[PDB]
Amino acid sequence: MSTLYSTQVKAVGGRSGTIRSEDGILELKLALPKELGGKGDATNPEQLFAAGYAACFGNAVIHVTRSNKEYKIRDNDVEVLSTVGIVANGNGGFALTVHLDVTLSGISQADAEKIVEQTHQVCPYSNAIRGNIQVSTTVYTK
Amino acid sequence: STLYSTQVKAVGGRSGTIRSEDGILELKLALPKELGGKGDATNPEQLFAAGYAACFGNAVIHVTRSNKEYKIRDNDVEVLSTVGIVANGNGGFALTVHLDVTLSGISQADAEKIVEQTHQVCPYSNAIRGNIQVSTTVYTK
Image (tube, rainbow over all chains, first blue to last red; front, side, top):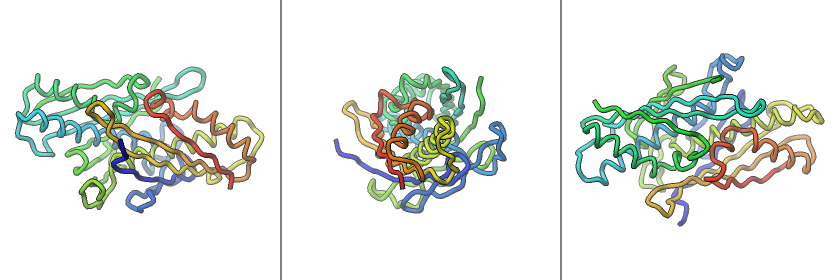
């Protein structure tokens, strides 16, 4: 299959530097959080990953709910709260952890759990990290 | 032990919003024009490209300063990530990743060896190994 969309982002200076997409849409400074000896003035790779994952997955949730043909939902009926952490692995190394809190409005609990299970096969983030990060997921309805 | 943890809330998918719990990261999201959107705002692929390129560059700095053959400052490292989204063969989507990594003031062979070492260190490269075959080109400027 051919690539549906591609984008480029330039990062200079590591976790204390800057990032800027080539189209200028995304441009912001980075800072080490206080937990890693920084100020926390600005975002960080974990925050950026958390945001992109939560947004991909929520969109895939909408996409799966609508392909199942049962529920009437609008986009804002889906909320994903991602928790992204960085832990120590091996000797001195670092690994990521991900937990997803998925809240669906106007859907039964069993259907929401089945929907969320389905979207893990859809969102490219989940497919990207399967087996390396053991993603945990809790499904809420409201 | 968990050394740092962050939370981001996303409402409405690729046309909605994101907001970190501490308020530091708050952005609108839009579908790109290639997918029929207006492209007013960022998207999950840009966010991933930005996070990945920032980790790898930071891990490149650490690896270079761990072999201790070159004295290098932060802005001597630049990572240009190319992230695409493609449909897989099984009713889902997959990411593609390419990294153009530019290291100032060091030889080509040392830069290639440093980048190879970094791929074992950056959590994002470890996060996707076996699912995404990352391609990498090393430049020395």
